[PDB]
Image 1 (cartoon, rainbow, N blue to C red):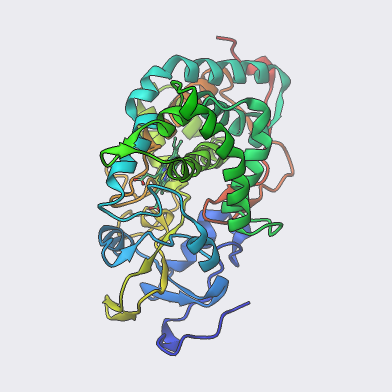
Image 2: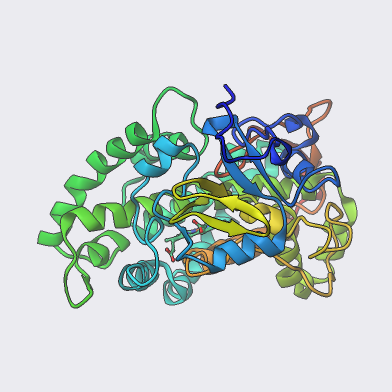
Length: 405
Ligand code: HEC
């Protein structure tokens, strides 16, 4: 539903890439985007798909525009338009130096200190979980593990009840992989009308979970209001329901067709760190944007005031000039170049936890279920969005080859 070409876009910088459904989806989801980095693709194109918008296709320009907030603002960082002008979360839809008050506060509820504390709670779900699993010879990897372990971790951290996950999940997915049952604006209010009551409770009866401390923190030098704490929370509810859980399907995905990464891991327990790093470049997955503040000429291409630019965080690490052999998985990559976690002021607050959670995951999974395969005959589907996704990942193993810890 290609938008017609704004008068100021050259016909020749036009590339019709569809970020919610790109042509080559079946190749996989990092395979479909990589088509942007092909030799017939200008560094910097426009698609008229999802309302017409720019796309930087190369690590250096993604990084660069990620660097330059005065020109490239995260006021509207979502494609489409409606979603971004809709998007208001906090710190994510701010620019320096607003952002910096609120980000520090989103950093109290999830930044390193929190992860250390949560250490054994993270350790004991990951091993509970695989153990309950390993005797069956079988799981849909998505819903058996990729979903319950980070999410339950985040409910634990947010002190939200677990009965609530299926609603919070379905609504958060409607902001990154919309079914088209509902607008973003729609998804988002509905999320807020869940939040808004808990926030109100928690400012009254102030707790030790992410929502009360966020509820009850201060910024700038005065009380955070109920309204900002609400937009403070709806980032969180997203990195916690839905970047981690997908990236997991991603990599078990991977661990499943490749004996030797599995085999190299079990006898390199300290390669796990490097491994996790490399699975971040190789299954990078987020993509969001910026809106131009002004008319601005970037790398010879006239951007105008208000135009949107997709800066796929996912691309940077996939570009053959930041890394030799982009598609090939290697564990001792001498420099894992990426922006999986973002680039700029907005560097993922949730990184340390994601990691944690990837690390333990691989250390526990390989530890008790070393050998496991794609359930057979199945072809694995991915979905494409602001957060790219795995639909379903049936896994199979001989239980004779598992280890109780
Ligand atoms: C507990 C929170 C949490 C977890 C888990 C998490 N994130 Fe984040 N992420 C955040 C928050 C909060 C921000 C906004 C911080 C700021 O504004 O400076 C953010 C920001 C981002 C950005 C910034 C992009 C933009 O608009 O610039 C990217 C990319 C990102 N996260 C990727 C991920 C990836 C990948 C994972 C999965 C492995 C993940 N996040 C897991 C909370 C999370």
